[PDB]
Length: 212
Image 1 (cartoon, rainbow, N blue to C red):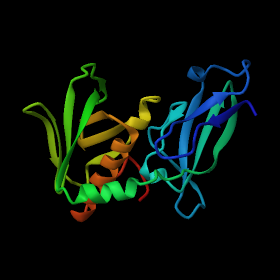
Image 2 (image 1 turned 90 degrees about the vertical axis):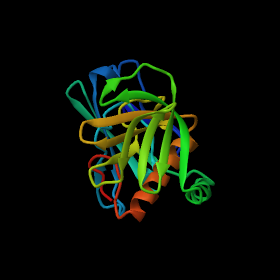
Image 3 (image 1 turned 90 degrees about the horizontal axis):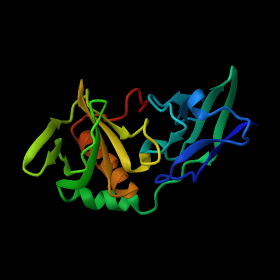
């Protein structure tokens, strides 16, 4: 019809809703929501906060069909990916190597703090450890939090084009960050590693409203 989903359907890539015609309303005037098919494929699960024309798959999306619903000028259109999101080749093996290191860190740039733009490009270290995550700038700790049921961590949902390289981390209520990695692979490794370490602490770490 009037819009379509475009993009490589793989972890590491970005998907976007794009107009098929110049007569299609501007995306800024549209209301968009993304969903993932459930694990048993029976229904679609709203990806909370994924309300932009751009959505970058994250690890929970692998093996799932993704969907975008759009309301435009009093009409509606339901779209989906051609198929299931492909995994990132070799990523599983990399994560296994990272597990053996105990605490690993990643160079990151902080782009948001508790919902507010953070313009500084200063490189931070994002530490993903057996029991805690911490974010540091040089010698100073910005945030440190042990895995907890309150914590959230997922691929970013509201900031496309950079999106495939960034994650959202809510350390605790009112304390959150959007953090950008040097590559998509590094971003996804950090998400998977944090989730593995959290799981070993009997914590199920996910994005807001995720079905696990």
